[PDB]
Image 1 (spheres, rainbow, N blue to C red):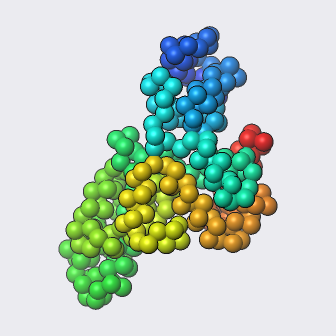
Image 2: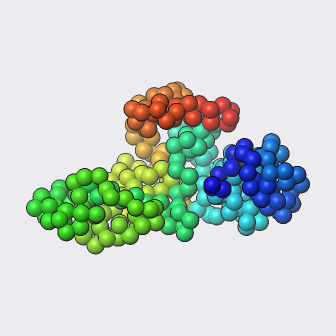
Image 3: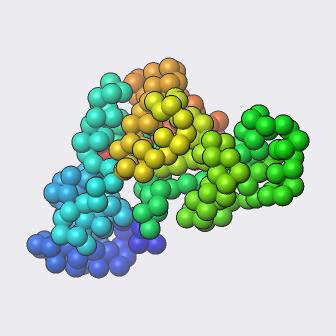
Length: 263
């Protein structure tokens, strides 16, 4: 579980060793102290990454690459731009990013994070063609076209599912999957400033910044959710974005804590 490292005592010593390998003087105690957090923050600042103190996959990539971050990784400047376009403080934007985004917008192999929703495939296929063809495709490929919620698999295979659906119809397939750092759904392409789903997907392939800006436009689409974000109404924003059970997952509390730590 070396994916992220906040304030734990673990093989965090390894991290500290690696930090010392790039010009740091951490004690290598194995405990994520404030010294360790400051070293991670320094690495993020040097790489241009989002400065949060969290040893994420992006920070680890920077550490293994001599302080250079991958161009598709989300940067502090990206978050500043998102906050500007949203008219909120950088701290609010950073909190929302920390809580609401998925870890990374791309998988371990660099493929974009995808989840194919087969019931959306069914709805789109039925709407575009006869309900009869929707039923036939349900019978033939129930994993790709199906009235009921999808039979998902691991993250990378979702791209294979998307290609299989595109084999049936490209537009429907691209509209029937969610991509990227905030798992924007394909059919919401126009809401995020794209003419069709395929273009939103391709642009999302450029980097996590496109994901963030599409997410910003998505927030701007919901006037009440945008207002809740502006008012730092964490409970309201969580209810509108995360759903009715936002409390059950401490989403509003997580947003509040992140904001406090980014003041």
